[PDB]
Image 1 (cartoon, protein in one colour):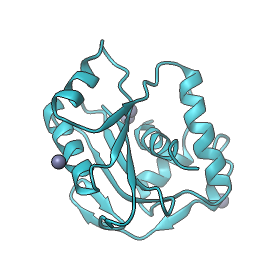
Image 2: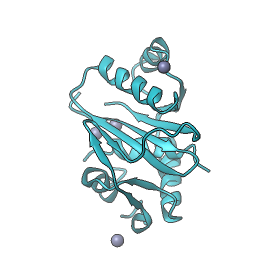
Image 3: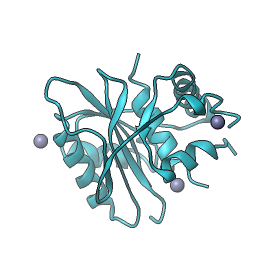
Length: 171
Ligand SMILES: [Zn+2]
Ligand SMILES: [Zn+2]
Ligand SMILES: [Zn+2]
Ligand SMILES: [Zn+2]
């Protein structure tokens, strides 16, 4: 891939399906986690749980055709399940609507509105560099790998963006 020149170094994790969740590891209370969150109607929302101690994705949740409140409900549940993992949320949409609903549901988040190509490239370039270094590990799932393999800046990229938002927190 032109953007992800380090695709061969991506670590491919075994996982168990649990509905909309791909689960690599259950919550370890001795580890700290964050979540990268992208929001979609028939477009997908994707929430990626990163173990900040290992640098590996512990869980990835993906859904479409779910109502706005159900999406936010799933995000709240996933955060809570991994120790109220803080959420790096793409809050860019109509007004402050996304942030309002996250604040109203008590979700622990940091806003990172992907409002321009500069912000998108900042996130994707970081993911790509970590991947080159062998530091990105994701569930070995066809849908995830296809989005990464077929990624172009200008054909869904919601998984890519969610992963990039999570890995923005990893040194
Ligand atoms: Zn290859
Ligand atoms: Zn809670
Ligand atoms: Zn999409
Ligand atoms: Zn998206």
